[PDB]
Amino acid sequence: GEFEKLEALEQLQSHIEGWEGSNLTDICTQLLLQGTLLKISAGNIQERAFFLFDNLLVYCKRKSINGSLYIFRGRINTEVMEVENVEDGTADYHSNGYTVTNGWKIHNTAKNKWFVCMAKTAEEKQKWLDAIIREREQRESLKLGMERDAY
Ligand SMILES: O=P(O)(O)O[C@H]1[C@H](O)[C@@H](OP(=O)(O)O)[C@@H](OP(=O)(O)O)[C@@H](OP(=O)(O)O)[C@H]1O
């Protein structure tokens, strides 16, 4: 049930070193998807481990008894995250001029920051976009349900 999932969140966070900000068990309840993606940001191309929870996207560097597997790099409140598809073959400054396949863009609107994600396969891209949609839908459903109760 919910409580077992919270203990799992605390354990998951314990594998991320250099965590910044509020803890997962205070703001999240579930993991929709985790996976490795290529991230291109501010001219830099870097592979990152991404984790999409309800309300939060986290990305980490993979670490090269010690429980650390990931090094915290960033987090985005999904309420201030936008996503844009990128068509295969696009090559522009967002990808440093490299050709994008299986990619998309993420907008951190709280930082006015954009970056590109690329997956290795089309099916993996589709899993990510589907998970992003599902996280947003679940969050909106819960919010609108509460607002409709209050209104
Ligand atoms: O490794 P260096 O040389 O420091 O380059 C960094 C990394 O690409 C960062 O990505 P990551 O955090 O995944 O390691 C980071 O921010 P983002 O997390 O915002 O992409 C920086 O962009 P900006 O600090 O935003 O300009 C960029 O300058």
Image (tube, grey):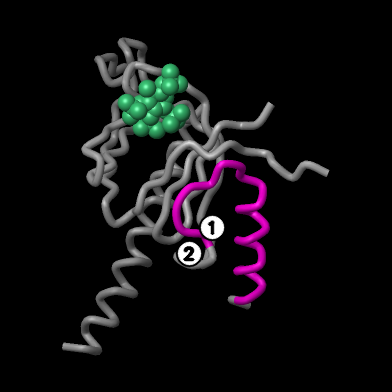
- Residue 145 showing in the rendered view: yes
Q: Is mark 1 within 8 Å of ligand 1?
A: no
Q: Which residues are magenta?
A: 3-24
Q: Give the secondary structure at mark 1.
A: strand
Ligand 1 shows up in the quarter that is top left
| Badge 2 amino acid | Cys
Would you identify the image quadrant in which residue 111 lies?
top left
Q: Which residue, as the protein is rendered here, is positioned at the far left? A: 151
Report the disc number at residue 31: 1
- Residue found 25% across the figure and 76% down from its top: 144
What crowding class fits label 2: few (fewer than 14 Cα within 10 Å), some (14-19), or many (20 or more)?
some
Q: Are discs 2 and 1 less than 8 Å apart at CB? A: yes
Q: Which residue is mark 2?
A: 28
| Badge 1 amino acid | Leu
- Quadrant holding the C terminus: bottom left
Q: Looking at the picture, tell me which residue is in the foreground, 65 or 102.
A: 65
Would you identify the image quadrant in which residue 61 lies?
top right
Residue 98, placed above or below residue 15: above
Residue 35 painted magenta:
no
